Length: 50
Length: 50
Image (cartoon, rainbow over the protein chains, first blue to last red):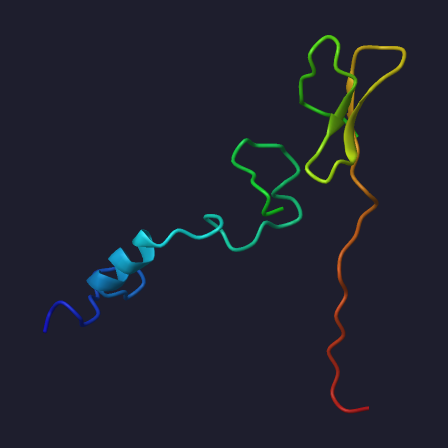
């Protein structure tokens, strides 16, 4: 059962299958929030999130 | 405020997604000025029973 138990070596205690599950799905943006000072500069990566 | 954008020699105003002007060209010199509304933010009150 080493393929579904948490691995202490990983930084945030996520199972190997969970890594594939998170990486397969893409969110609206890399970060959930865009803070007030984050979008002062019009970097090309700034989408409709902010 | 100041800006770091770049207009073409003929284009006058910068229009954003919401069709509202955000970059303006000075009527008497060649510089670009950025528009951002007055400082805003939601306030939330945390209180126990009155």
